[PDB]
Image (cartoon, rainbow, N blue to C red; front, side, top):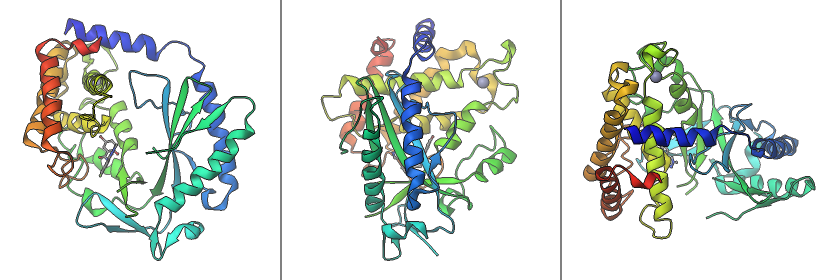
Length: 343
Ligand SMILES: Cn1cc(-c2ccc(F)c(CNC(=O)c3cc(Br)ccc3O)c2)cn1
Ligand SMILES: [Zn+2]
């Protein structure tokens, strides 16, 4: 636990210090935003959080940025695909008309114009050299030679969340019912990727919980109630990242993302709603409990999506047991040796 705060300390003195990347990424995103608004099918495109041109998926490499473009779709009609609970067909009741296939909205057609427009504005820049990669995040730019930006297009609906989210977000005992209501009055977002099916994105709700995360309204506003909810999250993610880097060559960890680690983390927060159970001085315990809960989801092949509870990110179909037994192998090995992968 003395070693964990060393790691947290290291990450900060790399988050913090001066780096021109923001300017380069700011200058390219606002060019794109304009030329995007130029075209009718994207006239409403905008950043999911202005002034937040900076969101880093990867907490180790701080040269890899990731921003999301929203585009409202009024009068949406949603249709759940194949009893999946999580994936849907997008329909209507129209600027996006050039992208349909019958009553159904095609993500392929829609990204394909999103991409081609972007590939065009990028050579309007003799300021910075910008390059677009082919895919296999909708679009990825390499700015100069170090920085890379992952762009994501997301439909936005201001109507209330899809029926599958009803018993979800069980934060009543921790953040409170009246907060849960507020958050569910926020819009929801749909991003592609199986059919032309879309799925919900809740990065905006995650962020809000994280900036206001205690049962106490004054959690982390003074010395007397500093917790370690965020710290346990960063460590969970850094664990998975570093592991994924290790076996970037093999294919064993390709099915895991930061979001399996956020999902399991918020579950713990729901099991442990008191700030007294996250005191900044129990950081070693609290992290261990997180490690133990993640693991337990791996073994039992059960980890409920935090927002759509009948949807199991670890079901034997979504990720096969062989790779979950491998992820178990390395994390357990790290925890038994005080986490050498952190260096
Ligand atoms: C990266 N990735 C995501 C999915 C996915 C799939 C199905 C599905 F229903 C959802 C719903 N999103 C979340 O649960 C979510 C939870 C947190 Br915590 C923060 C943001 C989020 O968007 C997501 C697949 N790959
Ligand atoms: Zn706190």
